[PDB]
Length: 288
Ligand SMILES: CN1CCN(CCOc2cc(OC3CCOCC3)c3c(Nc4c(Cl)ccc5c4OCO5)ncnc3c2)CC1
Image (cartoon, rainbow, N blue to C red):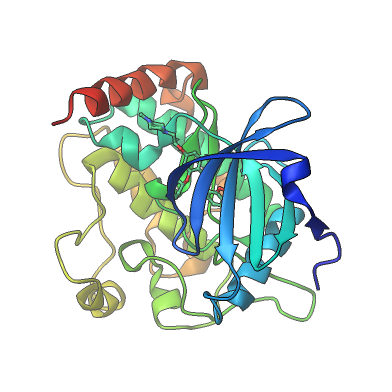
């Protein structure tokens, strides 16, 4: 099971104020009392959240096996009475979805964000892991513009005896057709979700965003794949099209997409993304 579970978290960390909800539990800011670095603490009431427990175990397992600058760093899991503390690196720049709220991105920002997402997917997929919930809300940034994949709550693991998954998980607007159909699928599902995320970064919202999620559960397998419509560069449109193939084996790998024209021509230093982070802080501060 979970061999490296720890105890007595408050000997090592200080729990500070609530900073969000992780659907499983609450998320708190915290301090590593050893380094004085800020951490993010997700507290899960084990007494309450009873059948997502197998998902909790899954999230912990996957995280404890990841070591990448492009994946939210995992400190450890701590048992404390009826509570499980999952302690991770704090990322202060908000999510990519947050950064969209004040207005449109330009294609340099879109490419920069996508390139780092792609480095994350390359890492995960090389580790036979599948994120299965790629969307802007699960892409978090440090206050200086580093970009990491977050929320491994439904991440899947492939093995020598299980080469495909088939579980119905993810977020409907971003889900690949084969996942909705619960066919046998793999990392190529993440590549479809990446394509929807590209549209989301460009347009602000995924295709079908105004419809009830249950509707899209039939629309996505039925309809032709979405395309990126509007006045965007040809390489961006082709990048999206490449990802959004109904046939999974025809989608490129993350490795391959890192050499796409759109990425090569437009991605720049992640530090430039602090402009976006500042735009959000400004916007959020004057929001009524
Ligand atoms: C103007 N600003 C307001 C302050 N803000 C800081 C952003 O704060 C976070 C919030 C987190 O919680 C998430 C809840 C789900 O949506 C995304 C935000 C962070 C986070 N969450 C987290 C997730 Cl998603 C999954 C497992 C976890 C987690 O914490 C420990 O275990 N992780 C890291 N940093 C967070 C910072 C800036 C803008």
